[PDB]
Amino acid sequence: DIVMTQAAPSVPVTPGESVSISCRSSKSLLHSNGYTYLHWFLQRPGQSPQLLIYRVSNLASGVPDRFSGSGSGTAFTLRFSRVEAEDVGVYYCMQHLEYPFTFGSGTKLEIKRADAAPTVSIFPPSSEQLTSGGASVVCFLNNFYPQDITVSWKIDGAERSSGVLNSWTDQDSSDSTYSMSSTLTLTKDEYERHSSYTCEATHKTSTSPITKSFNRGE
Amino acid sequence: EVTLQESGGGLVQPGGSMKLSCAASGFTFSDAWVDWVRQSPGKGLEWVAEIRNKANNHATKYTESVKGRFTISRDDSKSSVYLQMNSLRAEDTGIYYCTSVPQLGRGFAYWGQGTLVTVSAASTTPPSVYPLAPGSGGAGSMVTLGCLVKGYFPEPVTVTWNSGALSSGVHTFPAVLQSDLYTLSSSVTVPSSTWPSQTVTCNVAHPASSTQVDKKIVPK
């Protein structure tokens, strides 16, 4: 099998500047007929892949002029002349020379922007959930940048780690921020043995943790 | 208008069988070869099989791991291609895409929207939908509401707010799989001048169980 390598798992870039992504094959992708069968695909968050460039440097229809490609034999480059916030996604190279066709592991393009503190919102279990014997406390940490953030749950001061479900969105294509959901799941019984529930977030934007909490008995 | 539309995916029993279909339109199907490519967290995009056109003897090619278990076929009169999968294993779980290769050279030119195949003996279970409303008075300028979609299987579920009228301030998060069950959160952020004055409802649909639920976010 031909191995397609995309060394960088991601590349940070500022909207407006030029950038390039590389790919290499374990074998020359030149076919007997003179063509080099290497293509580039874009997969935006939650969508299917879409063709960007076929045969090293031919742009597919509908693909923006800012994309270009170059390379020969075993090394290839995809370039953006001016990157846009909308370009967030994973870019893949693929060899279409021999069976089985193979894809590189991809390079995610990350858009750099100004720091942004998360908007933290905490939600006590809904009445509907409590009557059903459940008690999930939800915390949304929305629209922040950079992408890393840490969330710690505190039940009456004591930290909780088990029963925490965490989910993160991909980078937003309009404002380049990130968002995260953290749900602390308890039984209704467990829930009523304590009183203070706290969602604590640590992000580079704050020296101190961003705390949001509420009391079961209120 | 070029389109490829997959169907037939969903939850399937390990060792069971399932046939995916792909309906094509908007391009010379007869002049094109058709491929199936799947996507999983473990392998990324993975080529699965190809079937050529009549002129090229309808020849078939398969990736090693599925040879003998999967069968790709096509019906030129219906401009469609199929992938019959048998002896399904956990490693076959993923999103399956149909893509066409017109022979006027263009690589994988067109892709379908994909169909999710989940290999599991678990049962189909509908979600419970719970509204998430703020605890204190809002003010300030904006308010964030949410909906907790819990206890369902398999994926996917579709979540919208006010039937689609509210979408720019929405964040629907990837679902988290717990004990054979998914739990997903969706949040919407609107002006405090919008809610609680105007009704805000999250609409949840779970195709696998034919469940549909509208829940209104009420101030607590």
Image: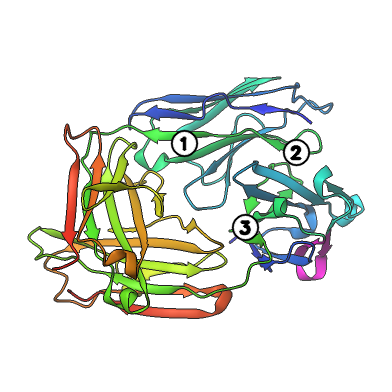
Q: Chain of mark 3?
A: B
The mark that comes first in sequence, 2 or 1, is: 1
Q: Are marks 1 and 3 in contact (CB under 8 Å)?
A: no
Residue sitting at x 23%, y 34%: A115
Q: Position of residue B184 (x, y in %)?
A: 42, 61
**Residue carrying label 2:** A101
- What amino acid is found at the position of numbered circle 1 in the picture? Asp
Q: Is residue B14 left or right of residue B117?
A: right
Which residues lie in the magenta part? B72-86
Judge whether residue B3 can be spotted in this image. Answer: no
Is residue A6 found inside the magenta-colored segment of the image? no
Cα distance between the residues tagged 1 and 3: 24 Å
Say whether mark 3 and mark 1 are on the same chain: no
Judge whether residue B144 can be spotted in this image. Answer: yes
Q: Is residue B192 left or right of residue A72?
A: left
Is residue B76 found inside the magenta-colored segment of the image? yes
Q: Secondary structure at mark 2?
A: loop
**Residue carrying label 3:** B112
Label for residue A182? none
Q: Chain of mark 1?
A: A
Q: Is residue A86 above or below residue B18?
A: above
Which residue is at the front of the view, A73 or B9?
B9
Count of number-bearing discs: 3
**What secondary structure is the stretch in magenta mostly built from?**
strand
Q: Position of residue A209 (x, y in %)?
A: 19, 39
**Residue carrying label 1:** A65
Cα distance between the residues tagged 2 and 1: 27 Å
Q: Is residue B142 left or right of residue B209?
A: left
Choose top left, top right, bottom left or bottom right for residue B63: top right
Residues packed near mark 2 inside 10 Å, few (<14), some (14 to 19) or many (20 plus): many
Cα distance between the residues tagged 3 and 2: 18 Å
